[PDB]
Amino acid sequence: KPWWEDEWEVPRETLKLVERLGAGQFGEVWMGYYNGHTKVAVKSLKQGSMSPDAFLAEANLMKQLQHQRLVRLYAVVTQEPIYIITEYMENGSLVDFLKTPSGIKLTINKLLDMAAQIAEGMAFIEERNYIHRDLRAANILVSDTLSCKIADFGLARLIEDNEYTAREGAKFPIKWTAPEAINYGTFTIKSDVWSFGILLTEIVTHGRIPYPGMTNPEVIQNLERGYRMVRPDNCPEELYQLMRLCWKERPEDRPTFDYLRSVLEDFF
Ligand SMILES: Cc1ccc(NC(=O)c2ccc(CN3CCN(C)CC3)cc2)cc1Nc1nccc(-c2cccnc2)n1
Image 1: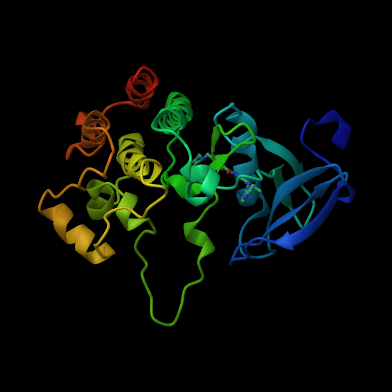
Image 2: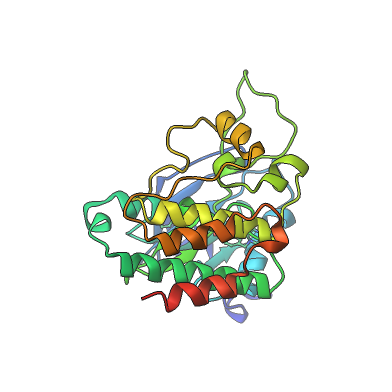
């Protein structure tokens, strides 16, 4: 099928990829320019590491799950080497942006609005009957207008295994993962709600790492004891209490992203 019949497919020629943001054991991620006028992020598949159709499976969801609060698919190149292209965000990821001087200037009101947007897109993902699995500030992109786009960069499969590790379990961010996911490998949307609560502490603490003063092993040990993160300084007790709802022990007792979105929106 001709590429101009499609809304996504573009001739590889339209792409001048310039910098290698991050390569792994399934392909690289470059920054480059589409027809010279737009800068874009380009995910490429390396041959052999996986099915061409398995790579495209992602691109395909992105077509189907378009939404203002999701990172929007920009273009795709199907032939090998395969590219998935989105647009580049000069503000970067939420966790990065928060630590910038302009990020640190953000008001609690603006922070809460971004949280609301993140909840909003998660609510859409829930509504479309998917989950995220790695919902945290590192997979959130900040737009030019300072709104938040939910991304999934495949952060986990992006790290190369070393001589010292041989886990054949699951891969997940210890400090963001609900205990039922840690213990029983059961990841659900309610599992993402947990992550969202931890994400909230990142938002309200300039992108600070969760569970300050605890190693990932320590974190898991304390989770077994029912331990919950301490309310970040200056973080409003009400917001914290909202976090505590995201960290209910039983996943079904945790709010929905709709409720989260709602509470967040009319918070002030
Ligand atoms: C180049 C690319 C290719 C694919 C994607 N895809 C996604 O971001 C994504 C988002 C949501 C889902 C939904 N998914 C449903 C299933 N569950 C299990 C997970 C979530 C899937 C993929 C993004 C990008 N964009 C991207 N990638 C890496 C870095 C950047 C980037 C851009 C600007 C500034 N800095 C970094 N941008």
